[PDB]
Image 1 (cartoon, helix red, strand yellow):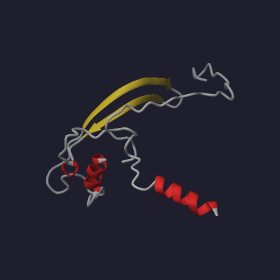
Image 2: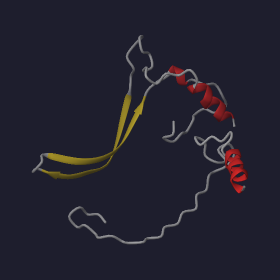
Image 3: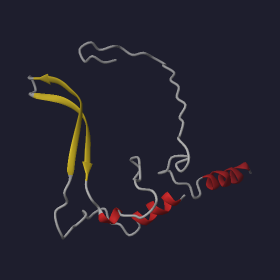
Image 4: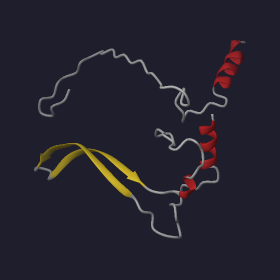
Length: 51
Length: 78
């Protein structure tokens, strides 16, 4: 019954976890690695100067 | 670690239905505006668009704490 063990893993992950605090707040800078995949480059609107 | 303790102590027994200084004196709010852009001005509807960053600052003696941390830098969660 993998359900119970995995539920325990998630509950332990979220126990005493504060989502108002960024990771490594005390002693680090949070480094976010970003990446974009463009599935469609939409129409360009001249009138609104936007895309 | 202890920023969690500070945050929990600040919010415990706190009523956000009541403005600070509810029955003492008016709440003073200082406002700043950064104008990113002033958009098109269509006279057909007699309106114009504007995009801004709107800053407001005020004092809440209930949000008073003592620690080595001088400022709590928070996102929209709180």
